[PDB]
Image (cartoon, rainbow, N blue to C red; front, side, top):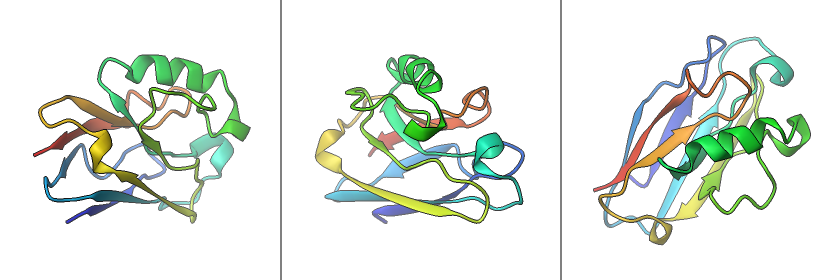
Length: 127
């Protein structure tokens, strides 16, 4: 209940668009995998979390950071939690404190790979 397994395919699609984080969870974990056959330089997926208002700035500063920085600006204060950039057959997990979240606030999860954020995004809420 304090974790979720998310897949990102070769067709730039996450296998979920809504994540519910339970109230009693102290820690929340995201296990990201990548089915398919494409490398990370063309189809690298990451799971990034920020407020709805902050998403765009993270996506823009992210694309401008390059592949070596997992398409994320280093020390970006708007990023609550993030996995690394993964290619097909690779896996990565991230655990964050639920105390960094506010109940009732609109959160967005997304991939920061260039031109993929529009196709790879969804909501996260603390209920």
